[PDB]
Image: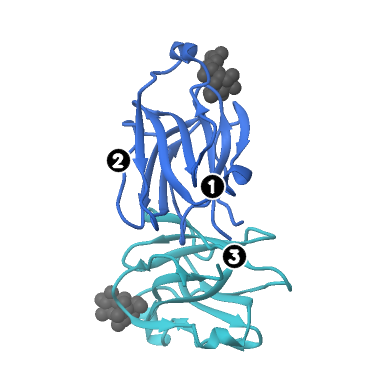
Chain colours: A blue, B cyan
Amino acid sequence: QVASEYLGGPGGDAFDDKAVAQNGDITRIEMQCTDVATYIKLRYGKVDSRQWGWGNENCIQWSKKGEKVVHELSSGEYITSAIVTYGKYVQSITFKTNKRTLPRCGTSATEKSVTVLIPGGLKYISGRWGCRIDGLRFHAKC
Amino acid sequence: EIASEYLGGPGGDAFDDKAVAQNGDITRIEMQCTDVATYIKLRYGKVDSRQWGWGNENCIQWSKKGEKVVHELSSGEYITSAIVTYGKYVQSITFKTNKRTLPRCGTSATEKSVTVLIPGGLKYISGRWGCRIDGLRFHAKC
Ligand SMILES: OC[C@H]1O[C@H](OC[C@H]2O[C@@H](O)[C@H](O)[C@@H](O)[C@@H]2O)[C@H](O)[C@@H](O)[C@@H]1O
Ligand SMILES: OC[C@H]1O[C@H](OC[C@H]2O[C@@H](O)[C@H](O)[C@@H](O)[C@@H]2O)[C@H](O)[C@@H](O)[C@@H]1O
C-alpha cells in the first residue's frame, strides 16, 4: 500500500507489520510512555504484533522506561493522523482517530515534528527498534 | 469515499473535480508557482478541469503570479502523497507518485505542513480557489 517516509534514525533492527496486519484492522494501540515513547505494539484484529521497543529491561541504562498505555479502538475506529517528533530515535507519538484524539506518548516534544495524515485509516506500521523506537513508517490501506 | 481533511482557509469559491474526473485517471498536473502556489489544474484522462486559482490578472494586486509547471504522469503512475503547507491559503504543494518525488510548487515558508497519504492513488481533488488556492482536499481511489 501507500506509505509515508521513514521517520527516525538508522539504529536498531527493522520490523514490518505487513503480514501480521493481514489479521485485521487495528483494534488496539499499546505503547510505553515516559518523556519519550519506548515501545509500540498494535493489535491487528485479535493478534498483537511483537513489542517493538524496550528490548531488555537493561535498556534503563540509556533512557527512562515509562508506563504501559493501552488505547482500545472501537469497531469502525481508525487512526487518521500521527504527529511524530523524532531525531536519532522517535521521541513522541500523538495519534488521532476518526473518533477521538489520543494523549501524546512521550511528554517531550522538542525534536523535529512531522504530521502524517492517513485518510481511511492506518493499516500498519513498519520501522526500526531496539531499546526504543528507532523509527516509524505509516502504511495506508491501499 | 476515502478523502483527506480539507487543508486551507474559508475564502474563495468551492470547486470539486468529481464529475470531470470521470474522464479518467490523472495524467497531468499543471500548476502555477512563485513563492506560493497560485493555481492547480489536473488532467483526467484527456480532459482538464477549470483552472483553480489565479482568477484573473488583477490578482497581481495581492500576490505574485509565478510560472506554469507541467508534470506529465506516465501510464500507471499515480499520485500517492502530497506535502502541503497551508494556513489561510495553500502555500506550497509537493506531490509524490509511486515512481518519483516531484518538485515543490512554492518555495520555503514558516506555515504549517502536513504529509497527506493518498491510499490507492489520487482520484481527484476538491478545494476552494480565487486569486490563489484557498485550500485543497484529496480524494483517494481506495
Ligand atoms: O533502540 C535504540 C537502540 O537500542 C540499542 O542501543 C541501546 C543503547 O546502546 C548503547 O550502547 C548506546 O550508547 C545508546 O545510544 C543506545 O541507545 C541498539 O543497539 C541500538 O541499535 C538502537 O538504536
Ligand atoms: O483566493 C484568494 C482570494 O482571492 C480573492 O481575494 C483577493 C484578495 O482580495 C483582497 O480584498 C483581500 O484583502 C486579500 O486577502 C485577498 O487575497 C477572493 O475574493 C478571496 O475570497 C480569496 O480568498
| CB atoms of marks 3 and 1 within 8 Å | no
- Residue nearest the viewer, comparing A84 with B133: A84
Label 3: which secondary element:
loop
Q: What residue type is labelled 1?
A: Tyr
- Residue nearest the viewer, comparing B54 with B45: B45
- Residue A103 — which label? 2
- Say which residue label 1 marks: A124
Q: Are marks 2 and 1 on the same chain?
A: yes
Where does the N terminus of chain A fall, quadrant-wise?
bottom right
Quadrant of the rendered image containing residue A80: bottom left
- Say which residue label 3 marks: B120
Q: Distance from label 3 to label 1 (Cα)?
A: 15 Å
Q: Who's the residue at 41% across and 83% down the image?
A: B15
- Tell me where residue B141 appears, x and y as whole percent: 56, 70
- Residue nearest the viewer, comparing B131 with A83: A83
Chain at tag 2: A
Crowd class of label 1 (few under 14; some 14 to 19; many from 20; radius 10 Å): many
Q: Distance from label 2 to label 3 (Cα)?
A: 29 Å
Q: Where is A9 relative to A141, above or below? A: above
Q: Distance from label 2 to label 1 (Cα)?
A: 20 Å
* Residue A88 appears in the figure: no
Q: What residue type is labelled 3?
A: Gly
Q: What residue type is labelled 2?
A: Pro
Chain at tag 1: A
Q: Who's the residue at 33% across and 62% down the image?
A: B87
Crowd class of label 3 (few under 14; some 14 to 19; many from 20; radius 10 Å): some
Instruction: Indicate the quadrant of ligand 2 in the picture.
Output: bottom left
Q: Do labels 2 and 3 share a chain?
A: no
Q: Where is B7 relative to A26, above or below? A: below
Q: Where is B5 relative to B62, above or below? A: above
